[PDB]
Length: 327
Image 1 (cartoon, rainbow, N blue to C red):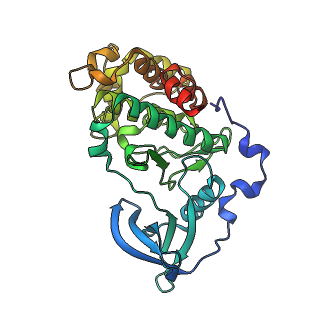
Image 2 (cartoon, rainbow, N blue to C red; image 1 turned 90 degrees about the horizontal axis):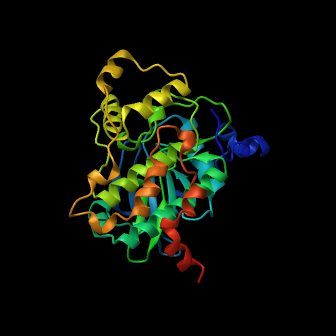
């Protein structure tokens, strides 16, 4: 399988662009940056609000848990390559504790609002607007030959006050090379595309569009998460109970994948469930025919059939947002 767009980005660019293993990190001064308070944490890092002692400006400090040097070089190089793109978090500095040699990445400060309280208050238009802004970031990174691979609400920072959005945590992102086989143990469970759940390793930028779709479905249906699987196998079953088993089997035979017997049995047979059946009194104000049409072009088994981020931004569902932007 190859990507339908931006397939040759890394083929055209110099090896220095994408050979992250050969990067040479110019370490800054650890003292320039002081931690003020913890604002987050995950499996690979702790995140703090900090201060730049010289300009006394706020910043974000991400202290990395121990991992192989390669993964560290990957995140940095990707951040450096994307620096300046729309709605991509900006890496400001890189520093290491002399003794421990524990790295910290320093980023511009963003005043994020917790999605668990933000989302149920967004109005129809707000959704349109933030999903458009997230699309700009995704089209930009794909255009630069990179896949994010962990798109989820937690990785989308929003400052509802200022209307500002940033795509963060590029720790799982990789460079796309035509025909390369990637690890399928990426993304977070609820946002994993079928390709990952069926061991299709030669995936591409379209993976991020599946994840974006899941996010979107979650916001317009107020059903977070939308596909609530317990383990990887159950995740596939949860998708199949909605999209239906016929499309899955068409997909598997097209890419010549055999599902493992246990899994096959878990999946079973299921008819497709119309998106309208998830409509209810709490979400109704969010669910236009254009919302459903867009969602439908995102959540497809076949990664090759999904809308690309560029196409997505021109869908009529966004036209007011576009108009607003054109001043």
